[PDB]
Image: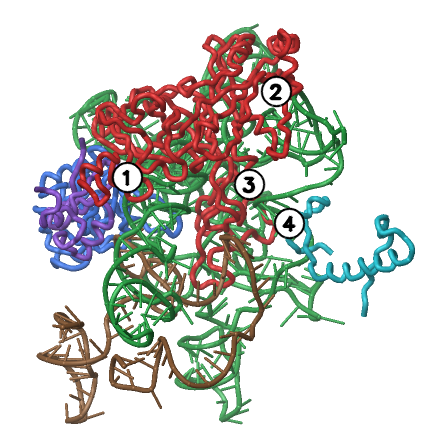
Chain colours: A cyan, B blue, C red, D purple, E brown, F green
Amino acid sequence: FNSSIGRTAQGKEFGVTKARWPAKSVKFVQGLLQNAAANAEAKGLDATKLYVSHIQVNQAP
Amino acid sequence: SGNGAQGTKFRISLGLPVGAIMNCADNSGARNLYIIAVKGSGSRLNRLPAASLGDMVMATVKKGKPELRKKVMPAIVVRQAKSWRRRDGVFLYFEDNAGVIANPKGEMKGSAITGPVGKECADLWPRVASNSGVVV
Amino acid sequence: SHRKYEAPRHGHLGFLPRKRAASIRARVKAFPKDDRSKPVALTSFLGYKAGMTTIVRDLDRPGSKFHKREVVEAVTVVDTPPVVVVGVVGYVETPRGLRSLTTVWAEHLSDEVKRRFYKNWYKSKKKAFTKYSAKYAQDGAGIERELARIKKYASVVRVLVHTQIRKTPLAQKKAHLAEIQLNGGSISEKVDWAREHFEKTVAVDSVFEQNEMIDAIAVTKGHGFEGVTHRWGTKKLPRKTHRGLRKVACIGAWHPAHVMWSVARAGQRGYHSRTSINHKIYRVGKGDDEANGATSFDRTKKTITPMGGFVHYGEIKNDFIMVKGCIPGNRKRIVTLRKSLYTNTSRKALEEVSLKWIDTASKFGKGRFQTPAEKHAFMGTLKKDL
Amino acid sequence: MKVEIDSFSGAKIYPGRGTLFVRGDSKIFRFQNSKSASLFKQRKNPRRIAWTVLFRKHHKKGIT
RNA sequence: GUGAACAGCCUCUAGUUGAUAGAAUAAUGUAGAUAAGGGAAGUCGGCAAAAUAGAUCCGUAACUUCGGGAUAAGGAUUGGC
RNA sequence: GCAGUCAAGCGUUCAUAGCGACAUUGCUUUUUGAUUCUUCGAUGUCGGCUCUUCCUAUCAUACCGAAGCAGAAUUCGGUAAGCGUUGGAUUGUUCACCCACUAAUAGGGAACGUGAGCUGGGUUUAGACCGUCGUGAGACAGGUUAGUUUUACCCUACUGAUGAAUGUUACCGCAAUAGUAAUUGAACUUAGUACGAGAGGAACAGUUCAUUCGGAUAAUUGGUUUUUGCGGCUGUCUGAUCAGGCAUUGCCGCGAAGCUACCAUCCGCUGGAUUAUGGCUGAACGCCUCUAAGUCAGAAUCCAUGCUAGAACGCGGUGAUUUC
């Protein structure tokens, strides 16, 4: 969902010309990314070896 | 410009287009001649032809002595009142807007140019700089 | 129908794509034709400008009306540190024109141009060329065959030079490079000329002398994404109009249903690599020595540096070389100085031309005075005690 | 040299600096900067202007 | 308060700080300006803009239905103590 | 509208120097006709302003030929579209017709170029008047005045500007291709001379400047002002003073920096190949001939040196290439 936004400089670390800083939508992703940590650690796993094999966003009504 | 050029001019800063009310400055009787063209100028669309110092313009009369009226006169600008530079790098400018009625070979109709005279119409029109007054 | 009133075309067509250039430095297209009976000397020079000053002269134009009688004239002054040459690179003949088959550096390369190849200096451990200095550690066992591979080959050999920023008030600390054609002769000592001038500088009178026609190649200053009235120069459409006041009016007809390359619309203005040719030189003056702004009969010991210095550049105590008119590009740039292409005929070169009054007046104001020791004893004693 | 001392404040005129105003009564008026000329369009007499040397000389400041 | 004035402009009592915000000034814009030397030469056409403009004194033509035109046109003065 | 064929004759004499009777063969789609093939669930259908290119059926420039051309002026033609072709009065005007200057003031086409570019003066609305016609409503390609000109943020085109991939990263270059620009005039001079026994009156090479266009630059001058820099002035408000607010930037005068002006200054290169045309050598044709092979000079023409961009899939030389 690129079109008609401005170029930046910080995006070329990932090999793209244009980027953003979606400061609100990030803030609900931390609210899960300690919650998923809050029960993966509290299952019996370690906490220094996790990674996200499946992230998913699909649109609501 | 042309008809009587015993030499040539440098470029002076041209600042009198068609429509200039230049005040006549001799004893030709009519004080106020109104410019209609110049002589020796090019052409591009919507550009007014502009009069220089010292050039021979063609310029009708407007008021005055009722014998040289309702015709077209050949004329010559004597002082300009636009800040030209000259080659010494000084910026002269007069106050008056002068002009003398002349006939085409280039020695004018009246008998006494009054007031000051721009000094670079000396060599261009030598037959009227002899009948000048205070020059420079 | 036709266009009802014929007029010339606004803007030159052989200068587009009017685009911002490669770097601050502009490349040079060509060099003079070599003639191998001449002494070996380099043909174009690298320097910085400071800002233009004013000059009166004494015209030797027999025939005109200001013969032997005064004028003013606009000189500019470009200045130069003693630039210093750090290696040659030979180009051989081929059906693709020129081709680099060599490179040979010095042994002690300077830190000002070990600066240049890096783009993030201080984090680096500075380790450029430190395996290439191993080759000179012998008698010449990797270079004497290499220079034999540029004596025998490489029908055109051009040598590269680099400035002295450390002797110049331009706070950049990062020098520059180029090439320069060598238009002397005897190709295999045209090589060995540069073999001598490793780790040594070269002057500014080494390439130019007085009263000759230099040729300027430089870059232009820039003004950003400019519109269409300043860009090309087209007419302002009248006050009555709607959707603008200073656009271009109509672009094309119906057919061709695609707008031309020849039509004048907005974009980039400035910071192109322009040129300007046939500029006259006046005074290749030495900076360190006696009274570089003292002309023939002013007899007043001063500099060419105006009162309070040049604006945005500072003072010149280095070498300087002054140029009639206006070289393209504003202050603090790398303007280069090509030599001629043809020996002139128009009696505008092929004379001697003198000099009568250089200036010192404060170009950071409407200045009045010529020496800080001259406004002192003119005004008297100020509230500042003498 | 080609020095000139002007007609409003005794300032200095060098070739490559300054203007000149003639009048219809044939009187030259050499100035240096437009400060010394825009006062003259407004008709400012130089003997009541606090920086001119024409005013400076007339009150015993730097002559003896 | 200035002023002739409930005009314009600043303050007192009373109310509000409500108009999505941060950063840097590119083009083209909308609103507001200024500009040498000519002065309608632009244009369907002085449209738009500019210029005088308050007050006091002197003056003020044809024409007229004698009431008017008329602030006709024109020129001078203007602070503070 | 434009171009040829003939040639009765004009042109003292002579058909073609320059024209061309009575005819006759075409070209063009800038005139205006003829037809109605496509658009009537809509191509915004007069003129002007601005802007680019194209065509020549050359008005000027460059070089050349022919003149009942002694010189200037001129009349035809040839290659030539590279570069120029204007300022005003009157009208809604394309057209028209004059006043001027210069080199000339050429004709034309690009949906009768161009309204998501503009103004709306005209006509194709509704208001109103007059003249004629009509009994009347009303009509008149007759006249006269006022009358809302809508959207782009889509794709493409173009003008600019980024960028993955190419062992990395950095520097230095190379040039396929594309664009390319300078144009004309006056005086001094040659010279009152060649020509003409007279009136008149040139040319080339030099100059020295100018006209039109383009690229830059801000030394000096001018325009700019929120640097709100300094000073002045008004009304008000901080008890008075010093210092300040508020007056859409209160107003004024000067104003450095910065940007800019044929409103200032500077700069705008020279070699190769050619066309017309003139020749040499030279047949065909024992001569004769610029041609049939060869061959020279030759235009503002073409291509190169120059001037700009550097193919983001065209490439070359060089440095360093993680002891964690």
Amino acid marked by disc 1: Arg
**Judging from the image, what secondary structure is the residue with disc 2 in?**
loop
Task: Give the residue pinned by disc 4.
Answer: A8
Amino acid marked by disc 2: Leu
**Judging from the image, what secondary structure is the residue with disc 1 in?**
loop
Residue C107 as seen in the image, left or right of residue F163: left
- Evaluate if marks 2 and 1 touch, with contact meaning CB atoms under 8 Å apart: no
Mark nearest the camera among 4 and 2 is 4
Q: Are marks 2 and 1 on the same chain?
A: no
Question: Could you tell which of marks 3 and 2 lies nearer the N-terminus?
Answer: 3
Which residue lies at the image location 56% right of the left edge and 40% below the top edge? Answer: C17
Residue nearest the viewer, comparing F200 with B109: B109
Q: Distance between the residues labelled 4 and 1?
A: 53 Å
Using the image, name the chain to which the residue with label 4 belongs: A
Task: Give the residue pinned by disc 1.
Answer: B11
Rate crowding at label 1 as few (under 14), some (14 to 19) or many (20 or more) other CA atoms within 10 Å: few
Which residue lies at the image location 64% right of the left edge and 29% below the top edge? Answer: C125
Task: Give the residue pinned by disc 2.
Answer: C98
Q: Distance between the residues labelled 3 and 4?
A: 22 Å
Which residue lies at the image location 22% right of the left edge and 51% below the top edge? Answer: B59
**Circle number at residue D30:** none
Task: Give the residue pinned by disc 3.
Answer: C19
Quarter of the image where the C terminus of chain A is located: bottom right
Q: Where is residue B36 in the image (x, y as percent from the top left)?
A: 26, 53
Residue nearest the viewer, comparing D20 with F231: F231
